[PDB]
Image 1 (cartoon, rainbow, N blue to C red):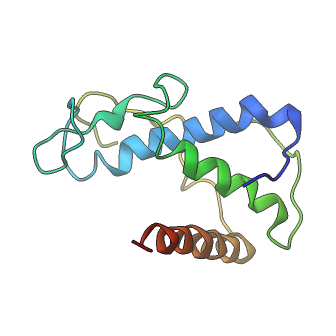
Image 2 (cartoon, rainbow, N blue to C red; image 1 turned 135 degrees about the vertical axis):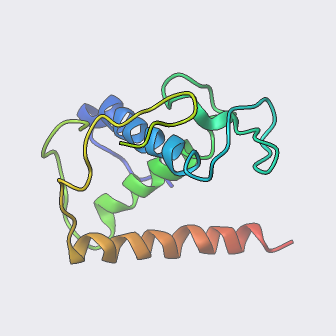
Image 3 (cartoon, rainbow, N blue to C red; image 1 turned 90 degrees about the vertical axis):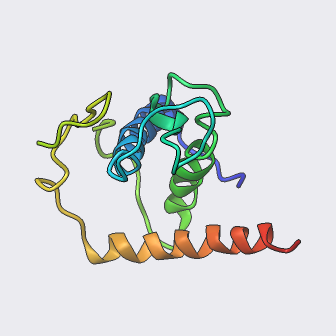
Length: 132
């Protein structure tokens, strides 16, 4: 939780979370639903279509608790990463965010190895949530 991050990439990681959040619009628009007041998937009520830096920490609380600690542990997951760069068709059902073509950009095997370790951490917090 309390892993210190460099102060240059504070807002950059928020736009990086916003580039994550616009895909968080997209993966839950690919289920075929729509915006709504409540958070009900089967009733086309998904309030998380507004972006990251736009919404407060009630409709943007699930990704902000996730994508921050996905970055917070990634700097100290037994590897090394630092400042490298900036915060860088299916017509959707109300907003179409696609600033970059993420299939023109490649991933690697040390990339997905830290993804499962971050998936190990949060699922154990999900096990810590499933104590009761």
